[PDB]
Image (spheres, coloured by chain):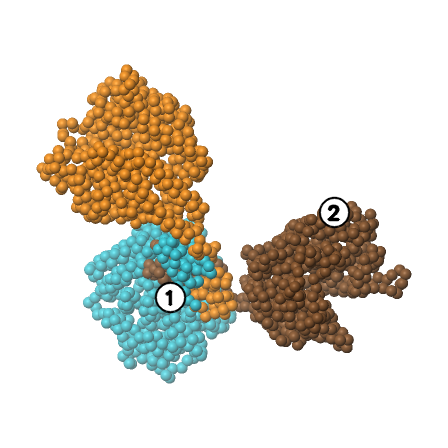
Chain colours: A cyan, B orange, C brown
Amino acid sequence: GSSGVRLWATRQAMLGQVHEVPEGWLIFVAEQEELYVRVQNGFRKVQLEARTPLPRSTIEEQAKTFLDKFNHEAEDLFYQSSLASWNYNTNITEENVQNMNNAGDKWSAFLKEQSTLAQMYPLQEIQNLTVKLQLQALQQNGSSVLSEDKSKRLNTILNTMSTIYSTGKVCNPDNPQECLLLEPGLNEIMANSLDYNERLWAWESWRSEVGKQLRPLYEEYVVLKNEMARANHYEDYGDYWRGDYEVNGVDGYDYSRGQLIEDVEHTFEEIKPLYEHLHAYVRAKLMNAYPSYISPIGCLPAHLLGDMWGRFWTNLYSLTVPFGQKPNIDVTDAMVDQAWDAQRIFKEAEKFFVSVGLPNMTQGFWENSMLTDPGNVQKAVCHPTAWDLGKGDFRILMCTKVTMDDFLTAHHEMGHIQYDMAYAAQPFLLRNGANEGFHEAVGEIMSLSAATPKHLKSIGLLSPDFQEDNETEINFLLKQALTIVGTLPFTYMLEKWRWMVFKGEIPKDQWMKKWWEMKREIVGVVEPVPHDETYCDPASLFHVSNDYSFIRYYTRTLYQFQFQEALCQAAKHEGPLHKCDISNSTEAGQKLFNMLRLGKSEPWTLALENVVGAKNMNVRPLLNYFEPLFTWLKDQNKNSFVGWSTDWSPYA
Amino acid sequence: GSSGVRLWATRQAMLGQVHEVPEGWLIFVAEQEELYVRVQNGFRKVQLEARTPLPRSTIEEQAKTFLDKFNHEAEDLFYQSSLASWNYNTNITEENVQNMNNAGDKWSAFLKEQSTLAQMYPLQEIQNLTVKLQLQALQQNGSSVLSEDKSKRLNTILNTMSTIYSTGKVCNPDNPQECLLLEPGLNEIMANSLDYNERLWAWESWRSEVGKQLRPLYEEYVVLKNEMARANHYEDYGDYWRGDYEVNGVDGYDYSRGQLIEDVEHTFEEIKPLYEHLHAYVRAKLMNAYPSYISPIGCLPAHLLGDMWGRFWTNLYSLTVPFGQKPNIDVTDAMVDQAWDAQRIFKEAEKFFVSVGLPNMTQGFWENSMLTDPGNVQKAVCHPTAWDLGKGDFRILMCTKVTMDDFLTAHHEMGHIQYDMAYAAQPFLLRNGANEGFHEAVGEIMSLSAATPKHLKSIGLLSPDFQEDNETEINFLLKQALTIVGTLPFTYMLEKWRWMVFKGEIPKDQWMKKWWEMKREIVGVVEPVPHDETYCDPASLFHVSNDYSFIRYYTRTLYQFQFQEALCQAAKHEGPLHKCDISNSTEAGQKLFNMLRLGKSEPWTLALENVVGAKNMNVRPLLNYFEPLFTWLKDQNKNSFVGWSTDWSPYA
Amino acid sequence: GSSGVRLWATRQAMLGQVHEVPEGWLIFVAEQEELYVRVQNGFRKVQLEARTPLPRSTIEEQAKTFLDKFNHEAEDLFYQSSLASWNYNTNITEENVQNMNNAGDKWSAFLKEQSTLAQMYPLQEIQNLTVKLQLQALQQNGSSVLSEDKSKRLNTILNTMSTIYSTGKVCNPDNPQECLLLEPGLNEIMANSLDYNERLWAWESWRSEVGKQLRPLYEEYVVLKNEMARANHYEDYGDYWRGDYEVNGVDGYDYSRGQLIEDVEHTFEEIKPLYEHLHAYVRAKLMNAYPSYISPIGCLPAHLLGDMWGRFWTNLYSLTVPFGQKPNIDVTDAMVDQAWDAQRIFKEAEKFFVSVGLPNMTQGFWENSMLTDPGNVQKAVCHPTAWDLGKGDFRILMCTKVTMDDFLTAHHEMGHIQYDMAYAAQPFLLRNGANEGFHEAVGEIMSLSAATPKHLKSIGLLSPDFQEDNETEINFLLKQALTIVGTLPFTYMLEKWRWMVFKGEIPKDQWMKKWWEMKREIVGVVEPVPHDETYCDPASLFHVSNDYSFIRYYTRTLYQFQFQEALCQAAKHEGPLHKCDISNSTEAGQKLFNMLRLGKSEPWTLALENVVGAKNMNVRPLLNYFEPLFTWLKDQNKNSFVGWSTDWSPYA
């Protein structure tokens, strides 16, 4: 049968009424706070533990209520800052500048108030993974952990380094009044002009007037960040940046900050045979252009890698082309013939996104964002940016033209937007990518998919009569290797160098003695002229001098290769990975959106495991993508020396 | 999520149907006497304690029937005994005396038989608190816990000192044939005559005469009082008295015997600053009367306190009046001018009770009680006493004359009788107050309200143009302090003295030395002639000789002040507490009657908490009542020593 | 007041909704499997034991199914086994001999297999007393708890002594070929011939041929009987037998094996004065018969008691009759006067058994059982046995003749089967007596009632004119004392002797000497010829050699006395207890049937309490039964010295 639970006022009433209480009927005493079970000819007291007072809101619940209230206020405040940011970037005016000051101060003050209001909430007793992740992402004091003077000094130094890099100007000895900046002056000169002396001077002059100036600033920046990290229970500032990839609280998915370093080391070792052959071929081709400036046995000059830091070897493609008479993959004729426009490019990207199974895109983007150049009466930023303004607002700000590149950037910005629309369901704190290499990877794979000849043929960009030969595939593989695989050692060595310089393993009087020697050995990049310790060459880059973790580029490339291979596997495509296309593949879009919606609500390991199939960052897709390149690279370097000599330098 | 509790005969159908049992459904098994909770994929055995036997034809019902039978027979027997007592009080004749002997013997024999017949009824298996308390009162064997000879000699000694106290006579040394009794000779001598010689001689001669013949008797009485208290599971006879205040088995209101001791001590310690100032002023007035008989730092003489044992300082109010030029408040002259008798005393008094919300009081009292001296045909005792005969019969014995003081006494007696009929619904055992300080407090609270000029003005006793300035307020407050507050230290020390005299910590050769040390240090009064252990001065009081608890008076004062303050708070009175009146406030009467009807069934702490809100003892209303007096005493004691010194004595 | 149980998926929802949970409503969460009770201002956690993995198949269910399956099949196998034994017992034939050989083999193998199956059903987790008790009987391995060789040799030694006792023959020295078996060649000559020499020679020869031969066999039998007793968790084989009387787990009726020894000793000690008077008078009559062979103070001869073991003094009733001239009570000649046979004896037995109120029994037993020897064509056994063949089949083996002795044994036999089918509702294992001293007691009590002169007169066995004087009552009482009370000391001591023989307290070189020492001090009987430890006189008993506990007879005597006293109390018998008759008393049969139906399921101590009113056994009925004889023995002991002497011997 079935029985209920009885309750009376006094124990005397319980005794007088327990006679008619059937067996199995629980008796609860409000006066005595006791529990009894009606047994045969009696009632047995049920043991009860210590009194537990009613919590109006547990400490976990108090954090939940605070986080919800903060997120609700953050959505409006961030949207106001985002729209003010949009207005400034559409038109740069004095009124536009001042509302950055107001929005920035208001957002920072609100963030500081909530972070202080969140710091008392303990993360140990909260078992809610989403709530704990929100609190730790909100409790990051950062520079505020130190004193006011120390925090202000660090911010002022950081602004100084950014200002020096941005306004770094070099004047030629022939005309001291004539001076040029790094961009677009030094970058274009060292990417197109083939003069060794001009490139060498610009490389040396910039690293002199920037390195010498930044050397005390970067050194004080390093120590201030290191001491801030110590105050934040971090071994160094590199450990602070690796904390984004750090995962805790999830069984089977925990990731430590040291695991990221060892995976980067392991992946670089895997790419080392492929990069060595790529470097050897690029080295060999430079003798074909300049036989009396570089030696095949030695390394390659930093300024002769197509840029100053050796970031991109794409500028060396004209100097390293295997078959210059073979035309590259370019469909610019289709643009002019059919009068293609930027709005049409985005419309085709949306249509392609519909084809791959992903849903449509909001019309508020079209009515609030510009694609072409917005006339000339106003100044607008033409840099490719995708905007997540919050509360459903998604925009893109760039002077998009009608070039294959722009068609890829449009796809890239759509890929950024798709991520922004995807984790939008997650709370404001969790309404972002799991790490800094996910949002860029989605845009990159979208650009890679949009650049495939099959996708162009499907939408008519590529002529149906176009043929696919070995030379075109080899040149495309080399071009991708220079652009992406070429920058992998650059990201690998720069982030590594920043790691032990923050760890304090590099003595001050030997800084450049390590970087320039390590550059020659691990990567085989050699400085054209010697630099003493007064130089600050590693900090001459934008990201390092602007408080940016450079491990994003290596992680995003590792993710983008894994995503592309996983999409190809889900799209049952037949053919080489470089020719693989995800067009008309609903499996690819659905699989991609499975991790896209997660954002940072789940650990990045779970997001990665969702598509490729594992939490590791193995470069197997990279080897498979460039296996025909690797065999061709081995064929080209079958007689050419492979590797690099640490001893050799251009000045020696 | 809703469920209940299931049951089954045995474990065979239990585990054959546990699969069909939904999760969260509690299960009781009669065969195994076990409890289980159906959890997700399992069941957890609920811990069960020993089975409590169900109520049956046990001692519970047998005692309840015995209690009902006892109450029925005690109602008639007590009615007959109280009828005989009133008749003897109305008419003192030889036939009335024989009635007392017969009624007293039968009542005592009946009580002891009920006590014996309830002795083998244990309370361990009885859970009814009302029955438990009633049967405990029945099981109050008393001195019969010892041998009969010990009880007989203790009663014989008690009657010896009580008779000696009544007949205690001192003779003038020059006139031996003329002797003055304590009642009313010595009392009147120290109440009216201010002569130091006469008061000292009467004080010394009485204590010597009483002490030299009662000291061995008091010692044996104390030893015997210790003997049957130890046999009654008490450390002394003090714990035997404190058992009435002790509360057990009631959650949130349990009281210990030592708790009242510490509460009384703490209340006196905070009272001490007010008492020291009052003692300072009375000492200052003693300098005004007899400059050479009181020291500025010394303690007051024992015989110069206005009464016999220094209890009440009302007789000193004439010599210690704050302003003797101000005439005292007295409506007796107006009352006699209005042709009002003792019948009008109770008639206007009954108007007061129906004014405060208390209902009409039965006409049986009016036809069964006298308000005047019944001439000289039948001798009547004029002592104030209220009688609850039973069966709805209620009487009050007092020679109520047409005076202001008898008006208060008439107010007190019917305050007793109104408490008597308040808990008439309670059984015979429960027909009593929770302690000995409640009935007197009830008769005191409304007496003070009646003595207030507002009540006299409302009933026409006082002229509407009566002036109430600060001088008459201070005089009234000081008179109240002398009559009530002045005796509070004496009540505390004497009860404390009698408490340790039962405990035996103070040796029999130090009873008088400790008594005078307490008198000097606590009371601030020093004897005019030193007394050795031959003197038995504490036993010279009526209460000590007749075995009467003295903590009842101090507790009653604390009770009456708390009761009055709550009544004033309930009546929404604004102004000084001494001017507070409860007339035309029906809420106060109804609220007061809520615990008056409760009787002694509930703990006295619960009753005190219900009245004001303080579960424990408090003296907060004392400060509110005498705040103008305390400020006046502090103002007037700036030029005089505050406190006392034990070193000084009138004899040294 | 009523309430229920509430559930929540997670504790977060529980905390939010705990405010809406009324007091008395239980809160359960499946995530933590935690139970809480809603209390005043909070929730109290309910203590829960370890979570079981839903064991829907308990051992209790499996054991109950196994027991029911076993009982159903065991009934058939035992039934056909009982048929074959009855066929052999009614017709001894070679084909019959192999019938029990096959039937016993199958039954034994079946029993050991079910015992083996019950071995994996431990009793700790079984809560049903009936299931636990039945499986305990099933799990009784007995001889198979040891190794096979120990069991095989124990059986072989058991067979050897059983054969030796059966074939125990002694030959006269003058006639080597003239030899007499113990039954009936030896027993007849000693019980009929009173010659001291012939009885002494037969006693000596029997103990020389059998005692010497069985001494090593008995010692080896005892050693092995101690071996599996400790393997069965018993300190000795005596404790193994005492385990049947042990009651465990029954609160208020638990019995221990040691308690049986203490109570048996206590009963014997208080019985001793009555036995000493009987032994003194029997000795006194022995000097009357043989003055030069028995001392007035010494113990009785072993061979001069009517039994070579000294069991029964019934053969001495003629030699020790209180009055040899008064005729004895016997109505056998009246049966042949009325032309009665064994059929009429049983028919009258049923009429008596239905006059006591118990229902008539079926006709199957009458047509399936013989009451007379089946001629001489087929050989049959005439020993008094009861056949509990099962399946509602009950039979009696008796060659009943038309005699009072056969009349009483016929009453004894039908009482046995009337006990058997009374508890037919019990399962096959529980279809047995509570102890070994109950089945014989049931047949004894009413057979004595049938033998009462009132019963004989009621149904016409004895003429109504028969006079009932004290002389016949004393003669009847003495015969009862010789047959029943006389065997009590021998029964108690021999079981006491065999108990410590298994225990090993008395060494092997003292057993028989301790027996004879106990025969003198306790039994009061002395051996006529001294022997050595080669003699094994206690092992000459049938029960010792055939592995039968001897405590059954002493317990049955006190059990039957208690049963008879309760029968007389229920029948409200007035006068001497030996003349009490239960005939024509329906209430007495109903009270007996209250435990007859109970069977062995309940503890025998509870059954004894239900009959009389005492949980423990007592000798009170013995005093009431033999009070006239006890006074007669006391009066006639003017020359009969109370007790005996250990020093005197027939040979010394």
Along the line of sight, which residue is nearer the eye, B275 or A328? B275
Residue B7: quadrant of the picture: bottom left
Q: Is residue A330 visible?
A: no
- The chain identifier of the residue carrying mark 1 reads B
Residue type marked 2: Asn
Question: Looking at the picture, how far across and down is residue C43, in whole percent?
Answer: 38, 56
Q: Position of residue C417 (x, y in %)?
A: 64, 69
In the image, taking residue C573 as reference, residue B592 lies left or right, namely left
Report the quarter where the N terminus of chain B lies: bottom left
Q: Which residue is mark 1?
A: B1
Q: What kind of residue is marked 1?
A: Gly
| Circle 2 SS class | loop
Provide the chain ID for the residue under circle 2: C
Q: Position of residue C139 (x, y in %)?
A: 63, 64
Is the residue marked by circle 2 packed among few (<14), some (14-19), or many (20+) residues within 10 Å? few
Q: Nearer the viewer, residue C544 or C29?
A: C544
Tags 1 and 2 on a common chain: no
Residue lying at the far front of the rendered structure: C465
What residue is shown at x 36% (from left), y 24% (from top)?
B211
**Which sits in the foreground, C542 or C651?**
C651
Q: Provide the residue designation for mark 2.
A: C639
In the drawing, what numbered circle is on residue A156?
none
